[PDB]
Image (cartoon, rainbow, N blue to C red; front, top):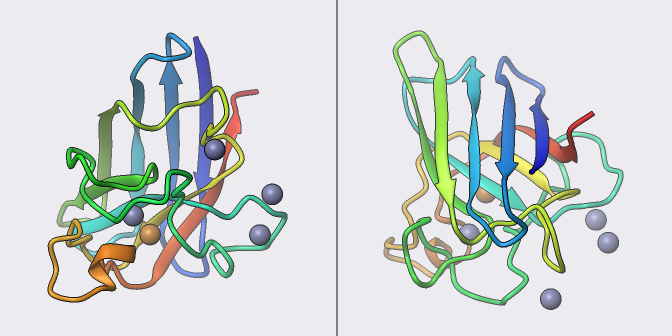
Length: 153
Ligand SMILES: [Cu+2]
Ligand SMILES: [Zn+2]
Ligand SMILES: [Zn+2]
Ligand SMILES: [Zn+2]
Ligand SMILES: [Zn+2]
């Protein structure tokens, strides 16, 4: 099996450790871990394109979209590779991640290894919003914490 870890950090209180595991090179990817320091409620959770040696959330930029699709939720047919939907934070600011996804992969041509995991200020509207921006980013507001998705050491 192949494994990865992303350490989420930002300029504020938001931080977390996210794990990835893929047991077969074309198998589903499981994603788990906890993020603390969040406001209660939904927060967009995305793999962004940025793979260069930049500091922080600054350049993370657009969603990881190697197939040039529109933005969606993780269960939508039309989605970016990086569209992992929302995570939910409880009253003391902790969001537990538990995701199984069929579109991301840790191996092959469009592997998410080296790309940037991002947790957002607000909910992702899942591409169902009333403007073109919804179909690009899901209108999830600022990037609160980010980290490179690295092969586990
Ligand atoms: Cu995003
Ligand atoms: Zn590059
Ligand atoms: Zn870059
Ligand atoms: Zn390609
Ligand atoms: Zn997207």
